[PDB]
Image (tube, rainbow, N blue to C red; front, side):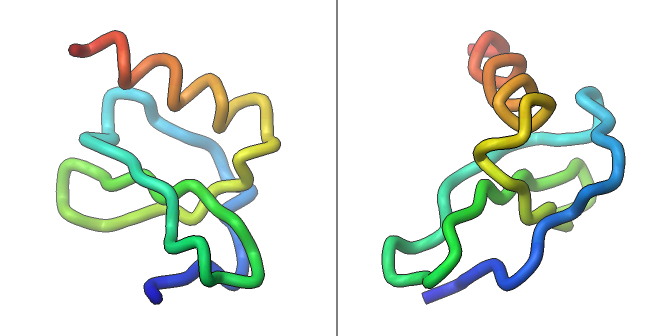
Length: 62
């Protein structure tokens, strides 16, 4: 369940996000969902460099 159909090819504000997770393994399309400070989420290609960079960043916050 909870799937991404399309990703956000816009720009990412690393200080705006609060978390991330990977959508269910059931989904035809894999995506990384970031969650912003205001509860909203961004569907992101896990193969985009800036996405992999957003992930790296976050994790270092812990």
